Amino acid sequence: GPAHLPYGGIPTFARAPLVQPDGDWQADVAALGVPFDIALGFRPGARFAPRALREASLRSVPPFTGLDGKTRLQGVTFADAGDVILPSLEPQLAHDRITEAARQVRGRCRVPVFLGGDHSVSYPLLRAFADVPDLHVVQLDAHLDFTDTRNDTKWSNSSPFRRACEALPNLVHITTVGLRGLRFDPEAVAAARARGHTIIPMDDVTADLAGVLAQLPRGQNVYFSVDVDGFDPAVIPGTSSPEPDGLTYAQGMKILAAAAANNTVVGLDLVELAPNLDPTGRSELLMARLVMETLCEVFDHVL
Amino acid sequence: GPAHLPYGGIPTFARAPLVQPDGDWQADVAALGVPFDIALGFRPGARFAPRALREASLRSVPPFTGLDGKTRLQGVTFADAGDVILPSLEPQLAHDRITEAARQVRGRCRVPVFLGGDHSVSYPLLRAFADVPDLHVVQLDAHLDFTDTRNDTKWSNSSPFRRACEALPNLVHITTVGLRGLRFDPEAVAAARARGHTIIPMDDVTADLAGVLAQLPRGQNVYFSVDVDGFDPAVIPGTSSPEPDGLTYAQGMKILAAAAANNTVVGLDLVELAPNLDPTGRSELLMARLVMETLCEVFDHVL
Amino acid sequence: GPAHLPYGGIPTFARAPLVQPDGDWQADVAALGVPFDIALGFRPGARFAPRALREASLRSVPPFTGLDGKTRLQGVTFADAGDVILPSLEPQLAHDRITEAARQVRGRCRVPVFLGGDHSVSYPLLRAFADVPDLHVVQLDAHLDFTDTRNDTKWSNSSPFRRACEALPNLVHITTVGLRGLRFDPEAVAAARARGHTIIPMDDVTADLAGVLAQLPRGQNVYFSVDVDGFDPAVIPGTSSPEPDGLTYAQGMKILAAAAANNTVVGLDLVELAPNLDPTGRSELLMARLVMETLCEVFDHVL
Amino acid sequence: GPAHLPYGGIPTFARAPLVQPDGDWQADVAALGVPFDIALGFRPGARFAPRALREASLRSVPPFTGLDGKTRLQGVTFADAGDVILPSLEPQLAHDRITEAARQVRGRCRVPVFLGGDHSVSYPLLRAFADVPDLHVVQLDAHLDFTDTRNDTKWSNSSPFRRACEALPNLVHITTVGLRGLRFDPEAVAAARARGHTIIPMDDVTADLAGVLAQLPRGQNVYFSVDVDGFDPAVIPGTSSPEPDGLTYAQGMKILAAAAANNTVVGLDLVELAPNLDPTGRSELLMARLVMETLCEVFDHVL
Amino acid sequence: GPAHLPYGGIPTFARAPLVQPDGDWQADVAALGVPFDIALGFRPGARFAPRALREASLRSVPPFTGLDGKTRLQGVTFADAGDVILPSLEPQLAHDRITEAARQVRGRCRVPVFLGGDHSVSYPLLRAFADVPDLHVVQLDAHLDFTDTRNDTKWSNSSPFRRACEALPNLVHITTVGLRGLRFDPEAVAAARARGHTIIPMDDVTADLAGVLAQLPRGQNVYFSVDVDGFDPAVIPGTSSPEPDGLTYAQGMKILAAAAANNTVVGLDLVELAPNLDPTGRSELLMARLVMETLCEVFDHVL
Amino acid sequence: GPAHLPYGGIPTFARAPLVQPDGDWQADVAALGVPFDIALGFRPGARFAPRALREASLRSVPPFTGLDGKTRLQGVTFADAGDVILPSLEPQLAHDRITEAARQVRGRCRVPVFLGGDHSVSYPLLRAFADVPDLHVVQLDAHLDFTDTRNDTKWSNSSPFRRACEALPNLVHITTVGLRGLRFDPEAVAAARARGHTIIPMDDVTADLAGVLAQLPRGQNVYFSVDVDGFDPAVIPGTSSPEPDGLTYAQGMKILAAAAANNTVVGLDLVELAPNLDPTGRSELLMARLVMETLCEVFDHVL
Ligand SMILES: [Mn+2]
Ligand SMILES: [Mn+2]
Ligand SMILES: [Mn+2]
Ligand SMILES: [Mn+2]
Ligand SMILES: [Mn+2]
Ligand SMILES: [Mn+2]
Ligand SMILES: [Mn+2]
Ligand SMILES: [Mn+2]
Ligand SMILES: [Mn+2]
Ligand SMILES: [Mn+2]
Ligand SMILES: [Mn+2]
Ligand SMILES: [Mn+2]
C-alpha cells in the first residue's frame, strides 16, 4: 500500500499507533510527551517541542537500512501514548501527573521515550524509575542542573537532578557531558562531586572524545537525558539558553551510541527543544533523528 | 477528568478519533485532509494546511456553549479520516485517490469536511458527489477558478470548477462570492455566465450584504467551497495569491450561515491556506474556527 | 539639545527617568512592568511585552502637539519604576510581589500604568487598590476572564477578575467590552451578570457605538484593563488567543476616551501583548501609542 | 507562446524590458528605482523595496481584462530603467544622481514611475519636474513631511516637500490625504497652510469621502506621491513607522482614481515600503498592484 | 564608473547582461534558472532559489582579486539566459522545456551554470549532454538520488541520476561525495555499484580528505551537480531535507577545486536551495559564492 | 534580595547603572552604544545591535564563578553611559558626537566597551585615543577595512581603520585576524602592508593558531575591534555580509584572551551585529557573552 510523505498523515511519533497511557497495549518503544515549559528562566517554547518532534519524526520512520546494507530497528514495535494532561500552573500537580503517566508507559514498553518540555520534567519522569537498582543517568547538557534553589523555587529547570537524587536513593550516579559557560552554581557543583557524580566539560570532549567515551558507565542500568543545548547552537539553535562551542550532532550521538552498547538503557528524555526559536526547522529534524538513531543503537546491541 | 490545553495531545481535527476512510465507522462529521499544493502557480505551502488546521482546531473542540448560554453541536459526533495518501507528482493518480477517499468518507458521515491543499483539489472532491441531484456549489473566493487551460495544464488550481462542471452534469449551479482583482480570464467568465452561474463581486458584498444573502440558493443541495483568499489579506494573510479588500471573517461567516439555514449542506472544503505565509498564526486559527462555526450553523438547521 | 531617535538610548517607558518602586520620587504617571506569562493556556510571549512596549513607546514620547496645534500632556511628569522582580514558578509569591510593587508605585504617582504580562496579573495589581471606594473596572477584552477554576488552577489568566472581586469587596462593578468567540464559561457569564456586571459583546459595539459609550460608568473611580486581544487580530495579531472581528484601534480608543472624560481614572494595565507573535512589530507600536493616547485623554479631563 | 509564472524570470517591473536611464528608447510607462533609505529615522528596509516591488509586479503584468470584459492598458508600452546608482552616504550626491536619472527617464516616457526608497527621495525626484507649469502634488501619507529641520539635518524623510517647494517655484500646490498620529510639527503645518497647501486628515476621509474627492485638483498637472504608510498598518504593515486607522486599499485607490481621471498625471512615486517588515509579503503584492491599477486609471482617461 | 551596491539594480547572475536562451549571444559562462520544485517530497521553496541566487551573486561580481594580488575570471564574460518557462504540473512537458533551454544555452557558452530547482531538474539538464563522450558526474549530495521509483513516480528528486543513466549511455560514471543519513535505498545503492559508480560517504571525507580527492576523476569530461544539502545544515540550513554532520563550505569547495583542476568541466547545476527556509539569508549568499568560486577554479585550468 | 531573570528589568549593559557620559561617575568598565548603520553597503540592522547586546548581556551579568569555583570580575564595577545622540544622516556631525562621547566615557572608566553600529564607527571611536602612545589595534574581521574610497565616500564601513590611521599617527600598528573572501582591495592591502600592519588570513588560524597567537603584541596599549563577521556565519549569522569558514567562538576568544593576558587593554568595540538577520537570537547572545568573557580575561591580568 502507498505510504504518506512527511507532510501527510496525523503526526504521531515515528508514525506509530496512538494509545492511552493506561490502555491495554504493549510495544518495544513508546513515546510520551510532556509539553511543560513554565519552569525555564529565559525563552519559552519547549511546550511546543513534543508536537514538533512528532512531526519531524515522520522523516525518520523505522526500520532503517544503512548505506552498508545493514538494517536496524527491524522488528521493533512503536506506540505513541500522547501527552500527559497538564494543568495550568500547579507545578506539584503537574509533577504527579507526569510521574503517573511515565509509570504506566514504562510498564507497557521496553524503552520509553519522553519528549519535553523544559528540563524540569526530568525530575517527575525519573520518579517512575524508583525500582531500578543502582540507576545511572547519562546527561548531555551545557548545564549541570543540580541546583537546590533558583529564583525562589525548588522546581526550576536548573534543579531536576538535585530533586531526583533526593527523592530516589537508587539514583546512585550521574554522568554529565558537555558542560560549558561562564557561570556555574558552586553549591550545585560541590553537591554533585560530593556524591561522586562525573562532570565532563565540553573541553574534555573536544580534547579527547575517546577518553570521554572511556568515562561512560559499563554494565549499568542507564537513563539518558538529552538537553538539546548540549549541542552547539550553530547545529541546534532552537533552545532557550544556548552556549557556544557545544557538541556536534556526531559527537553527541557517538556518546549515546557508546553508552547504549555497554549498558541496559531504561529510558530517554529529550528536553529544551524550542521549535519557535529555529525557523529553519533543522533543530527538530536533527533531534528527532537523534532519538531514532539512539534507539537503533539500543536495540542493535541489547542483552 | 482533566482536559488537554491547545498545545497538548495529538492533533486530529476537533480532537476526534482517527479512522480509515474505508474503515468500519460512522459519525455526523468526518474530516479528510488533502495535502496537495503542486497545482498552484505562485507560493507553495498549502500542503501543510491540513495539519495546521488540525492543530488550530484544538482551540475549537465541540460542542460550544455561547455567550447566550445555549449550546451548539451537542451530541454531534466527529471523526478524522486522516489524509489522502498522495503520490509525488502524478496529478491524475492524486485525483483518483482523492475522489475514492472522499467517496468512502461521504458514505460514512452526514457532513464531510475536506482540508486542502490548493484549490485544484475541489475537482476530484466534487466527483464524489456526482449522484447529488441539482447540486449547487457556494464558493467563497477572490478568483473565479473556471479557467479551461492555464500554463499548459488542465489541472491547475484555476480550473477546478471548470473540470468539475464538464465532468458532473448534476452540478447545475455555482454561486461565487468575493471576486475581485485586476485580471480575470475572459474565456472563463463568459463560460461561467453561459452555464447560468451566479457571480457576486466583493463590491456587491460591500454595497449591500443583505442583498447578497438574498442571491444565495434556497432549498437546494449545497456543497461549500471556501478559498481562504476570499477573505481580506489583513484578516487572513496566509495564502498564495492575496487580493486587497476582501471579506471580513464576519461577512464570510454570514454568507455561510445564511446558506446553511436555507439549504441541505452535503459537504465543505477549506482550501488555499498557507500557514508558512503567516508567522502570526492567525490565519489557521481563524479558518479552523470558521469550519467549526460553519458546522454549528449547519447542524442548527438540519432537516 | 539633540534628541535620540527611536532606536537610540536605553528603553524606558516614554523615555522617562528610571526609579525604584519604593524610592524617594513623585510623578504624575509611573510605569511598572510585570513580565509574567506562565498562567496563559496557549502561546507564551507576553513576558517580553513590557520590554517591547518600552521600546515602542520611544516612538511616542510626550508631550504631544496635534495637527490642530494644541498640546497634550504638557508638564505631565513620567517615571519608569522598572519591573516587579518575579521568581520562577511560585505564582502566589509572584502575586505578592506584584501587589507590593503596585502599592508602592501607586503611592508615588497619580496614574500608574502596568505593563503585562498575561491577564492573570490584573488580579495582584488590583489588590493594590483596596482603598478605592466603589472601584469600577472598564475592561477591553475578547474574553470575560471571570472563571472560578480552569485547568485545575485558580490563578489562570481566565480568572483574574473573579479572584479580584473575592479579594476586594470594594470592586463593585466591571464593564467588559469586546466579547466574542464560540465558547464562553456559562458559570462565569451568569455569575458576572448576577453580580450586576455589564457585558458588552463586540456585536453591540459594531451595531451601535453610541449606545455602548452610554453604558460606560460616570463619575466613578475607574481602573482600565486593556487586553490587546480585544482588538481585531488584523490590527493587533501579536497575542496568544486571537478572536476575529474585534475592535479597531479607533473604536477601543473612543471607548477609553469616553470613560476617561467622565470618570476619575485610578490606573491602567495593558496585558496579553505577545511581541514574538508579530514580526511586523505593529502590535507593540500601536499598543504603546494606545497607552500614551489614553493618558492624553485622562489628563485632559482630570478633576 | 508560454508565459512565465510569478516565480519565474528576471524580475523587472511589470516584466517590461530592461533599459538604461540615458539609453536609446521610448515607452508610455517607465519605471526607475531609488534604493535609498538612510534618511528615515526608525526602521530601515525601504532600500529593498524597488526589488520587492518588481518581484511583486509579476503578479500584475499588463494589460488587464476585468470582470466586465473591458480591457485596460491595451497597447501601453512599459520599460524598466533599473535603479539610480547611489553612493554610500553622501546624500547630496545621491540627490543629484536621482534628479539626473529622473530627468532622463522623464524625457523618454509619458508617465515615469519611481520606486523608493524612503520619502526623502521625493525631493530630488521632483526637481526633475521643474518645467511643469502649476505643478500639483497629490500625496497619500500619514505624515505631512513638510518639516524644515529634523535631527540636525535638512535631508530627512520628514522634509522632502519642504525642500522641493523651496527649490521649485512651479510646484504651486500640494494636497495631502490620510494625515493622522499623535504628533505633528507645528512649524511644518503652519508653513504648509501659509503656502495654501491642502491638508486632509484621515478623519475627513472616514467622515466624508465625497467631501475629500471634491477637494482634489481638476484639470491640473499632477504628480502622485504615495507613502505606503498612508494605508492602514493592518493592510500594509511593511513600513518603518505605521500609524493606526489608515486608508483601506480601496479608499486610497478611490482617491488616486479620481485624481487620475480628472488631471494630467506627469509622474508617480511609491515610497516607504519595507518588505523586510512584512514576512507575509502582502505589503509589496498590494502596493505593486496599486501602482498598476493607478496606471490603468491614468491611461483610461487620456486626452 | 560608479557601481551598484548589492541591493541596487536588476538581479542577474553575477550582474551579467540579460539574454535569451535562443538569442544572438556568446559568453564564457551562461546562467540558466529552473524554478521547479514540485518533485521533492518534503518542504517546497526551491522554485525561489534561482531568484535568490541571482540576488546573492551581486555580492560576488567577477572578476576577483584575492589577498595575494592574483586576479581570477579576468576577461571571462558572463550572461544570464533567464529561466526556463515552465508549465504548471505537466512534469514531462517541463522536462522537455528544460532540456531544450539547456541545449540552446550550452551551445552559446563554454561553461553553463544551471540554478535549481529541486534535484529532479538534473535529469532533463543532463539530457542536453548526450554528445559528451564518456561523461562523468561529480555529485555533492547527502543522498544518492539513484532510486527507480518513489511515492509512485519515476520523476521525483530521488531519481534524477537513475533517469539520466537509463537515457544517456554516454554517462558512464558518477562519483557522489557527502552521503550520510539513517536510510538508503538498497536497490538504488546496488544499481549504482553495478554500474561501477563511486560512492563516497561523508565519513570518508572526515576520515581522509586527501584520499577522497585522489578518488575524483582525472582527464575526463565532468558535469558538476551540487545539492546544497551535501553541506552541513549549520552552514546551509536552507534546504528541504537536511542531514547533520555534512561538508563545510571549505571541504565542498576543495572537492570542486580539485576536480575542476584535473578535468574538462562541461557544466554545473546548483540544486535544492530553499531560501524560504533560511531567514538569515546565509544559505543563498554562500551558495552563490560557491558557484562563482568554482568558476574561478574552472577557468584557472582551461585548455 | 531576589534578582531579575533575563526578561526582567530595564536592559542596561551587564545590568549596570545608567549614567551620562559627562556625568559625575566612575566605574572600572563603562559601556557606550553607537546605533549608527547608514555607512554599510548591504543589509542594515546594526543600528539595533546596541539594544540587542544590552538585552543579551542580562544573561551574562558579572561577577562570574566558573566550573573550577574561581570567580572573575569580582568587585569590578560597571556602568552604562547610554548611546551617543546621533543626527539623521550628517555623518561628519555623527563622527564628532561619537568622538566626544567616547572621550568623556574614557575619562571616567578604566576599560570602555563600545557597542556598534556598522564598522565605520571604529574611526570616530579611535579618535578618542589620540593621546595613547604607540596605540596598537587587534582587529577580528573577515575584511581588512583599510579602504580609502568606496562607492564615492570616505566614511563607509570599509574605511574605518584607514581613516583612523591618517588621523592618528600614534596608531602605529594593526593586527587583523580572520581575513577571508574572494575579493580584496589591492590598494587597501598595499597601504596596510606599507605601514607594516600584520595581515592574518583565517587559513593561518586554521593551519596553526599557536603561530597566530605568537604574532600578537606584547606589553603594548591595545584596542580590540571585534567585527562579528570575523566569526563563522554558522555561529554568528546575524551580520550584513557573512563569509564562510570563519572563526569559531572558541578561536576568536582564544585570540582575545591571549592579547589581554600581556597587554594594556585600552578599549574594545563590537560591531556589525545585525539582530534582525538572526531570528534564533544566538548571534546577540554569543556576542554579548564574548564581550563579558573578554573583560574577565582583561581583569585577570591587570598590572
Ligand atoms: Mn538541562
Ligand atoms: Mn541545558
Ligand atoms: Mn482564490
Ligand atoms: Mn480558489
Ligand atoms: Mn483577558
Ligand atoms: Mn483576552
Ligand atoms: Mn511620507
Ligand atoms: Mn509617512
Ligand atoms: Mn540531497
Ligand atoms: Mn540530491
Ligand atoms: Mn569590518
Ligand atoms: Mn567585516
Image: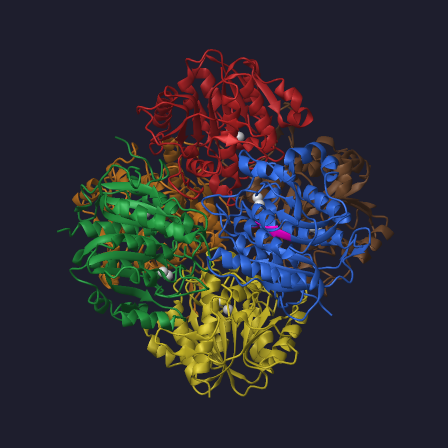
Chain colours: A brown, B orange, C yellow, D green, E red, F blue
* Residue closest to the eye, D152 or E118: D152
Q: Residue B79 location in percent, x, y? A: 46, 49
Q: Please state the total of marks drawn on the protein image.
A: 0
Relative to F71, F96 lies left or right:
left
* Residue closest to the eye, E170 or B231: E170
Query: What is the quadrant of residue F243 in the picture?
Result: top right
Q: Residue furthest front?
A: F169
Q: Is residue B256 above or below residue A207?
A: below
Q: Is residue E70 above or below residue D81?
A: above
* Residue closest to the eye, D254 or F118: F118
Q: Is residue C109 magenta?
A: no
Q: Is residue E61 above or below residue F138?
A: above
Provide the residue span drawn in magenta.
F269-274
Relative to F52, F261 lies left or right:
right
Residue D46 seen in the figure: yes
* Residue closest to the eye, F155 or D264: F155
Query: What is the quadrant of residue C251 in the picture?
Result: bottom left
Q: Residue C226 location in percent, x, y? A: 48, 71
Residue E148 seen in the figure: no
Q: If the image is split into quadrants, where does the N terminus of chain D sit?
A: top left
Q: Residue D120 location in percent, x, y? A: 37, 57
Q: Residue D228 location in percent, x, y? A: 35, 57
